[PDB]
Length: 150
Length: 149
Length: 153
Length: 148
Image (cartoon, rainbow over all chains, first blue to last red; front, side):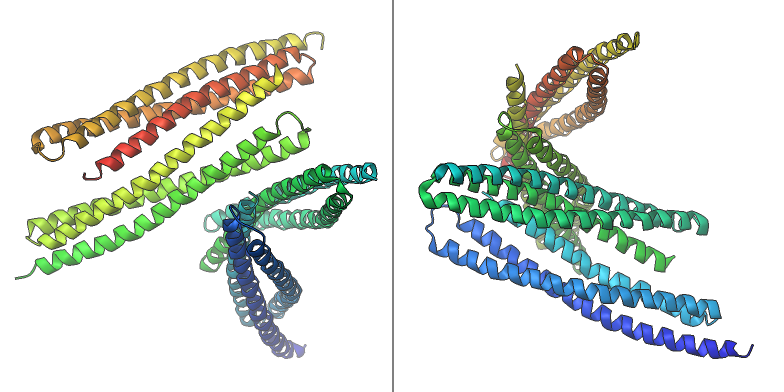
């Protein structure tokens, strides 16, 4: 069959396109995570300040800070929903590039496969690193909320 | 009238207790799944080097199952949290209903109950956040170690 | 002709390393101390529930207690490992101050030993806060054990 | 079953004796360590009181004692740690024995086991709190020693 080298050229176009698409969803996902983490930091600060006001106090400033907390929590939940919808797209992009690395290997393009496999591993590492910053921020928020219950 | 609003505060408090206890177990069950998946990642990483394919392929299959179970448990926790938030809303609206009409002590005990429960749930949530943090750390170690080896 | 500059480069490099290991250690001790307070609060929370409850509240809070002490042990081991590193930094900075003195770089000596004694006091002071927290944790545990045995008989 | 509870009663009796002995051995080690902490504290305050007028011979002499005193404090700490592991196994044993008692219908043997475990946990925690107090006073003495 003569369509072997022609299959190698087409599967290289797939690895090239899926890698581009993976970069694009990744970079969008990492932005969404960082903005969500920044919102979590802000909400955390407001809790610790609110807590600091409990004790010899009236109702104006506590209600005002709490109203800010209500807005900040809307912002945190908004940002969480944006990250979730972008996470599906990124996972589809990951799936595509994984199937493309496989197709490259099955047709003998091999070198396109390894470069795709390296790209996927790099991208999961980049995303997991900002994700771990998100988990840390979430933990400190939980700590701030527990301290507030005084 | 106060008899009816006290029946509401007591019933909504019971329902709040029950859904809280259900939510807390869903969270711990989710957290145990996160601990297990974390351990399997650390084990997999520790085997990179010494081992080759079939030992690693088998451990990886165990890892694939561990999220299937972790994701399952996450979905059950999510649906129990929805119910729990309705229970909180109910108990807050019921304490308010107590405050109007003058059932004050039924009101204050409801607010104290609501706050007590929020602390309990937040305390289990923070251990879940810690477990999630350690899982991400294990996954970062496995990814660096794989591109290295 | 020189040596005075070379030994001063040693005191400054070791002082930097001492500063860094100190900051990591004090942060580790402070994190351990917060964990002890957290565990203490949960014990008082459990104790306050003894008497008028059903095993929902007690079992769940207790499950949190198992996690919190697991975290307390984690933080304790991390502090211990970081203290080892800090002690190497202290030894280095002590011998560096000595070498500065033996070569006549007196001010390099005085600044190093002042730095060493500054850090030893800072570390000992957060250590004392840790002992206080540990004492209060034990008290919370004693109160809970008295309450539980007086609840039975 | 016609024969099972007599074996489980042997387990509750043996683990209960073993728990008592390890508890008393542990309390010995903690008290013994606590006394070491008190003495080291006194030597510190004695050393601290000498800074100034005094020359180094006798400050250096007390200081050498302090170095020896901490070696003993550390020895006593590791011996307490080793016995605490053993005591924790004894506690686990007795709680698994109380568990076995209930699932086989003993229970009254059970209630005494749970109370016994709670009692020894209280006894060990109380001597532990005295050692924490001693450690706190030691840290204070070392802070006082700071150089002044």
